[PDB]
Each structure stands twice: as C-alpha cells, then as structure tokens.
Amino acid sequence: ADLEDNMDILNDNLKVVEKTDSAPELKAALTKMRAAALDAQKATPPKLEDKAPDSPEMKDFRHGFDILVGQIDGALKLANEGNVKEAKAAAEALKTTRNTYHKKY
View 1 (spheres, helix red, strand yellow):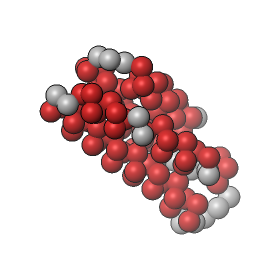
View 2 (cartoon, rainbow, N blue to C red):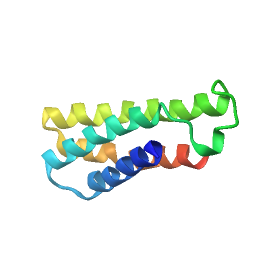
View 3 (cartoon, rainbow, N blue to C red):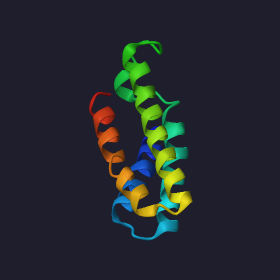
C-alpha cells in the first residue's frame, strides 16, 4: 500500500505544481514529490511482481524515477535561485515522465 501512497503523494503534488503561482508552495510541492519518488523507486508494482527483480521491466521501472528525481532537482535548483517562473515551466514536463512510466508498468 505504500507504493500507491507514494504515487498518491506524487500525483497530489503534480497538481500543485500545475496550479500554484506561489513560489513557496511550488518548492514545498517539488520537495514532497522528490521524497515520494525515491520511496516509490524501492517498490515493485503489483503488475511486475512475477518478473525478476533484475528484469528489464524492473530496471526500467526504477529508472523512470531516476529521470523524475533529476527533473525535480533541476526545477528546485531554479526555484531556489528565485527563477520560479522557469521552475514552474520546467515542472510542466514532470507529468509527462510520470505518464510515460506509469503506462508501461
């Protein structure tokens, strides 16, 4: 249930980064997303429980989170500089990554 929970956290906060025009809100959402992503990355989704932990499908499940975390960190770096409109624009590409990797797992 912790995997759904983290995905829940990820998706709630994706909504925040889409909708907010408050910089601190944007930063707090990016931060919560990062922790949630690293937690989800340790899980095995019910649909791949029968593949090997070592399978390409699992390597690829984890790697989607490496991409997301990289994007989140890039957006935070920008935001923390005060480049918050650019951070929000970068953050628009988060949902896309999540959708690409949530389809194939």
